[PDB]
Image 1 (cartoon, rainbow, N blue to C red):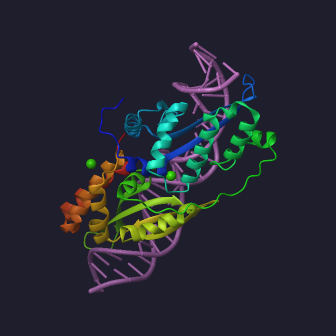
Image 2: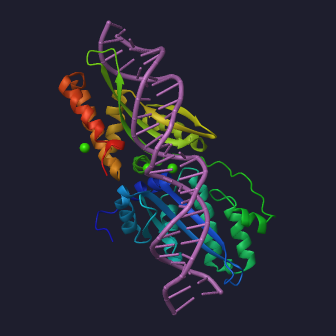
Image 3: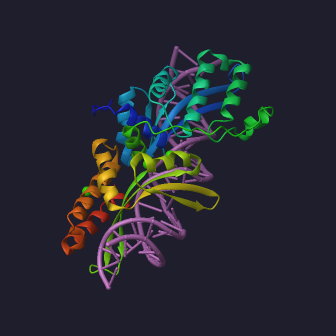
Amino acid sequence: ESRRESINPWILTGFADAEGSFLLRIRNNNKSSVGYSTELGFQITLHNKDKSILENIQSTWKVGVIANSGDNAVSLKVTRFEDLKVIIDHFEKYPLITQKLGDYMLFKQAFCVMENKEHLKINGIKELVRIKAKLNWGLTDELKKAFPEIISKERSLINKNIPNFKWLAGFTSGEGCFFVNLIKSKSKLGVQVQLVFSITQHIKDKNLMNSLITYLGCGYIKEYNKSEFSWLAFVVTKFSDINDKIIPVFQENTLIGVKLEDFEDWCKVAKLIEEKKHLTESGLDEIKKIKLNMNKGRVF
DNA sequence: CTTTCCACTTATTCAACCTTTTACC
DNA sequence: GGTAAAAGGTTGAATAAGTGGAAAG
Ligand SMILES: [Ca+2]
Ligand SMILES: [Ca+2]
Ligand SMILES: [Ca+2]
């Protein structure tokens, strides 16, 4: 229902590569003729502060329902079957490029099973369980028990290229960070101001992440580990690269959500640095206050 | 019988954050 | 030497992904 301008379709695909998810529920249901009912869909869950992105996607595609996900988050879910055609037409024309493309392909296979009403019979349920085994986190314990002949095997790697800077604006709206690092320094003011751009992602998309270096013509990859988990970040710390390469990209290709406000505050700091005001008392004061009112410091 | 919606749950991949060290001139 | 750039990380929660129940014809 939003009357805000519609979201650009590539920005939407990039935001979905970041934050979207495909869903296939295969549920025990003793009122169904086959003993199972299904539900197929696409969904995005965000913090409450970004509910307006969900409204804007809802009004762009003209489909989906919005509901709370606990007290601090909100979802857009599309599962009405005819409305899934809008989702398929979109991602066929503006395709995903992360490993999530493999989940879209499994969703589309499932759509074809359900469109033929095959899932109302046991052959169709078996084909959906085969599809679901490869989808996201795979089969539940109960489905593994009911369908032991379905082996869980690893998926082929997706290797696609960034299509344009609109996709990148949508993806950065999901995964990006515009950070102002205030480094204790042996300098006259005692504080070094360093702007840091990052995009963060699991190691499954290392090839895509490395390609950001050539696509943007700057930056580097940092590797991370915590517990059983590994991920990467594309990082830019060189001020001329931030000012001449990163900032113009998102000035031209507008971010969505609260993160736009953080980007615009970050650009105020970059203008001060370009003017060397970050090495003055008044400039440092302004930058300290900007830090306190962006990202985690922003009130909601 | 099946679809659709709305309330609700949960593991970790994200974002955002820090300090210290080295590069550069 | 002093400023910029990179290195070397930590961690809490907004994401992704999933689950429970039932209204409706
Ligand atoms: Ca993501
Ligand atoms: Ca995000
Ligand atoms: Ca501001």
